[PDB]
Length: 70
Image 1 (cartoon, one colour):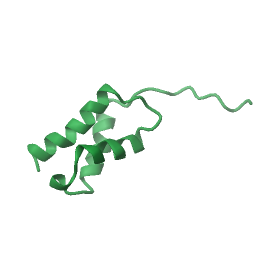
Image 2 (cartoon, helix red, strand yellow):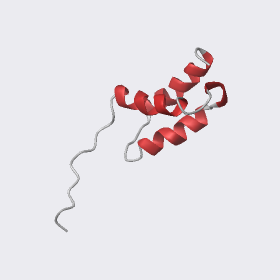
Image 3 (cartoon, helix red, strand yellow):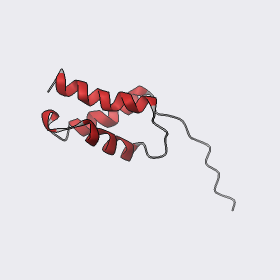
Image 4 (tube, helix red, strand yellow):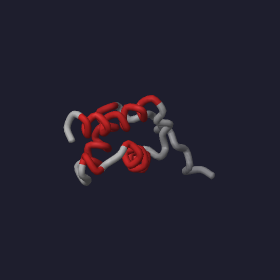
């Protein structure tokens, strides 16, 4: 053990979270995407994170883009 340290571990600001999703819908039909797919992909980019509150936002970011921007 020596090189293993890990010092960076913070949640991505909304600018980052939204960016991740903006990439998901940008690769799929909004009316054909569901909140379930957003959480799956989103986590893919946010694996080492405890997205709990900001998570409810992600799913809501697409669900609102499909109802107010299908």
